[PDB]
Image (tube, rainbow, N blue to C red; front, side, top):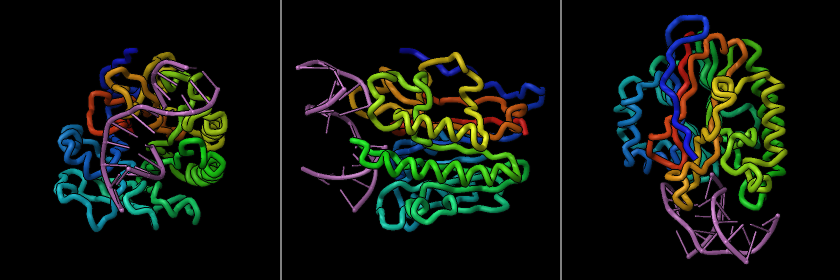
Length: 276
DNA sequence: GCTACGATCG
DNA sequence: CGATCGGTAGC
């Protein structure tokens, strides 16, 4: 019932210092989160890149403070075609991106504004807000179709440069990845299809659970807690947000934090330092 | 008031 | 189990 995120370890196993900080956050309503003092934290965090999930907001409405964000001058956004005030992702960065694509190159899955790929120098970044299988699992059957595709797309990317996948990947991979593993085997985020698909994901590319790789033992590390009950004040949550990065990035991997004390939404931000 | 983002205790 | 009372942000 504890979990206290450890200190920020800013060095690789090789030896050299950090040279890239990536923060990702499922803000649960961009606007609201903003009023909730989110940018103060952002400005306070100083990530070189900031991926945001569930922005649930279209560009011709984006809060003004955004542009006013200093070291994040390059802002890219994505929203659902027919879904007003739904899904939506946003990638922000200090250094400008060589190439920036939206979605995973697939019609039916791209129509919800859930993916953004930012190509860089030493690596590539994708930020995603994975399709919730919904309550009663009304969408689990479809979900798996996304996954089938998603891993397919990501693999072809990990063929040129080191890939960095982050966002609400919407899955409690292992039982260690949620406070109550047993009591949720028949609730979204923990289905054996989702979990399997996720594992299948790791192997296929392949990719690595940055955090898990740093704390294989460390339990109670949740990045999401439902608003229901006093969930957060009781740390009874799930860890649905990850930093999956190609194998080649592991000798450069510094840390993977779960900034729990960061208040703003049902999810907490997650930062990835890279000694690139 | 509803709709898409699950811990409780029968 | 599995029914459900039930915190949000946004239409």
